[PDB]
Image (cartoon, rainbow, N blue to C red; front, side, top):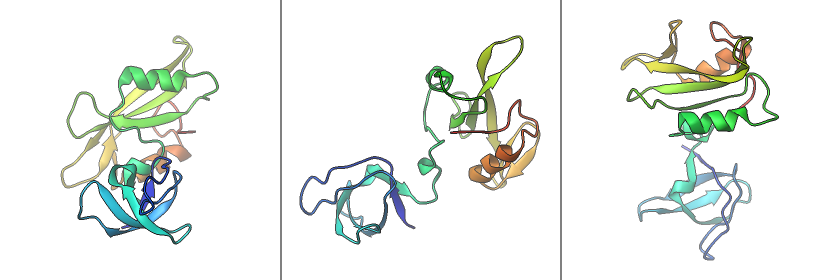
Amino acid sequence: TLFVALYDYEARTEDDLSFHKGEKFQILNSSEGDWWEARSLTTGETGYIPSNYVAPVDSIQAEEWYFGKLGRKDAERQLLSFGNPRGTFLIRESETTKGAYSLSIRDWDDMKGDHVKHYKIRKLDNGGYYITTRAQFETLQQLVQHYSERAAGLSSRLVVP
């Protein structure tokens, strides 16, 4: 598995690699602990890096529309920021049920003005992810790919992260 950087980091030591968010790496050694020996695929250089600054190249963690444990209110402030169009969205963890997620979208209703909708994304122990309309996806990336092409039940189609 390759890894990708989620934040910009200024090489501390000389044995420390310096890097920008978005850079990929191959893990040479990950046994000493919080710091890992790695090889940048952009420069080919070798050196250490904080393990909590990167995530697997396929993980949800590094997708840009995923905001881990964000709060309803927090995501509502984030999405409603001037400039964000209708369909802007984000996915966080469920604040109510353990092991599920919430798809938060910025939408425009006639009665309500400009607002946010929050749909729960359920999961089957031995099946896929699905939202209330009951169509499942093996992956949350697929799920997103899908509602990006067409609303298909949701109030709005997925536009921008």
